[PDB]
Amino acid sequence: QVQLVQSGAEVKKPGASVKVSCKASGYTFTSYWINWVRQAPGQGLEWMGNIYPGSSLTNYNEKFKNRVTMTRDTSTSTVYMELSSLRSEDTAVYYCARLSTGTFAYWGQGTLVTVSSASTKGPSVFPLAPSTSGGTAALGCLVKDYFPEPVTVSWNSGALTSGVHTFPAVLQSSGLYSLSSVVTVPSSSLGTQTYICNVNHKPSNTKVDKKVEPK
Amino acid sequence: DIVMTQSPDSLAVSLGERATINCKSSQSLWDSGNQKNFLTWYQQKPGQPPKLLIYWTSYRESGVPDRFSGSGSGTDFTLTISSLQAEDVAVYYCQNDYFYPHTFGGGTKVEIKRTVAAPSVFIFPPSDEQLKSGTASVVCLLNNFYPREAKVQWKVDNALQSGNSQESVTEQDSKDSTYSLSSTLTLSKADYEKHKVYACEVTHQGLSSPVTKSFNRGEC
Amino acid sequence: WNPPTFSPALLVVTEGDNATFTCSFSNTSESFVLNWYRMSPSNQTDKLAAFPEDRSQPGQDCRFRVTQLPNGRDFHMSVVRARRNDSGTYLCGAISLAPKAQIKESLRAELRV
């Protein structure tokens, strides 16, 4: 099949430069245009540039005058994207895509580049205890003060999926992220079923299974 | 440079009716050498790479359903969904595919319009485990409401808070087409120990009167 | 290179038969993809098949198929088990894979079932 696998996530400091790889397979790599598109959190897509692997022809965006650089490697069928003089505004998920006009469009899975002076910190998991209402009760976990993204939260090892709301993270003044995950259940189940949120933060080797007991 | 303006910014359509999105370009996207209007339409769901729907203004990519149809010529273009299904909720971008740069439009959020639904409001006092440190976090949860417009205000001993709270909303739920909001008021333990009444007051179209949920510190 | 030729301009075929078009080129390009297009009543264009074939590409129906003739310039856009739904207008087009891609599309030929 046609596949575009991008390099993994990276955290960089302001002023540094990142290089994202995109390995094409399943077609004549040297004949199709490869585009780069980024998306900052809470904003639309932004075209970044073009590269034709056949002759390394590039079409950069004027927004990144001398920061963007696209190259190719025919021996490994990989295209690279380099962005220098990084800012906090450059925090985004970056996509590579094979977009030759009139032909089918394929997309890489994306690559998250976090630009921040913060350092890796494991999250604290606080229980949001119920009591609750008359009919339904709500309980949750507060995952506070971690860097970088992402955190994976599940309930009862993934066995509790109904009424679960994991809210998107929020960047705080400390440069750390914070999210909460809630779940609504019948009021009669508070004392008949155990509830455990399973928080996982891989960059800091944090693994916490907090039991949410009522108050 | 091509400027792509998308109007409306957000669109609410009932399940099964027609949605129309507009895209106006600063210059003509017509190509005399290929006899095509080079404009592309994209669909992107949260947490997913974009998906190409329409290229060359009115050409459908393989696998794109019947309801999606592009139109327009020159500087005015339009994407139309004839039967908006649940799987269509996403942001739609028009893109200049004619001249470089291939600038995107601002996008248009397409949500399912449903009946008014009030939020279920909950307030969680800070955990005692958090009270081992120097900060205190109070969370106010708004569960399953429509429309998305909601107002949350924090009160400490009947003193309106400002500049010390953050919030975030989920995506429209696939089952009931509702939203959930989570707001976190952050205080220092010193400030938390100096006040008794904590409350969040919700103002929503589904509430006849604003709903307030409070608690007293140290009381259960 | 010249635009291809989609013949016959009108092909009337009974229901449930083998209707076959012919997309012929005078001279071919070094790198190109050939597409089979059908116009929908919404004034849209749908890509049914494409040469060379990509088995991983979704949306392809097993009914419509494109076949390269031995001379390499002519192609066979055949549909098997034709339905009354298939009645419409069709066309073939080629897009070169050069940096500056050029579109070369045929005229429209109508199908009746």
Image: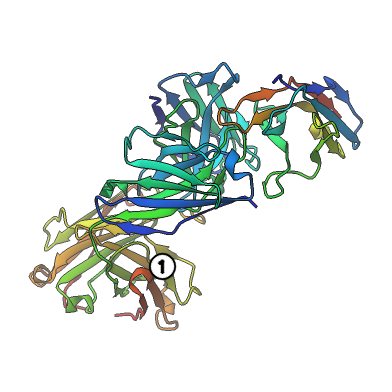
Q: Secondary structure at mark 1?
A: strand
A103 vs A9, left or right, is: right
B140 vs B22, left or right, is: left
Residue occupying the point 68% across, 50% down: C56
Is residue C3 or residue B90 the one in the foreground?
C3
Q: Residues within 10 Å of mark 1 (few under 14, many from 20)?
A: few
- Relative to residue C60, is residue C91 depicted above or below? above
Is residue B135 or residue C8 the one in the foreground?
C8
| Percent x, y of residue A15 | 24, 50
Disc 1 marks a residue whose amino acid type is Thr
Residue occupying the point 7% across, 70% down: B194
| Percent x, y of residue C14 | 92, 31
Residue B109 visible in image = yes
Q: How is the image coloured?
A: rainbow
Dividing the picture into quarters, in which one does residue A31 lie? Answer: top right
| Percent x, y of residue A176 | 25, 62
The C terminus of chain A is located in which quarter?
Answer: bottom left
Residue B179 visible in image = no
Dividing the picture into quarters, in which one does residue B100 lie? Answer: top left
- Relative to residue C40, is residue B157 depicted above or below? below
- Relative to residue C78, is residue B177 depicted above or below? below
In the rendered image, which residue does mark 1 sit on? A152
Q: Dot 1 falls on which chain? A: A
| Percent x, y of residue C101 | 59, 28
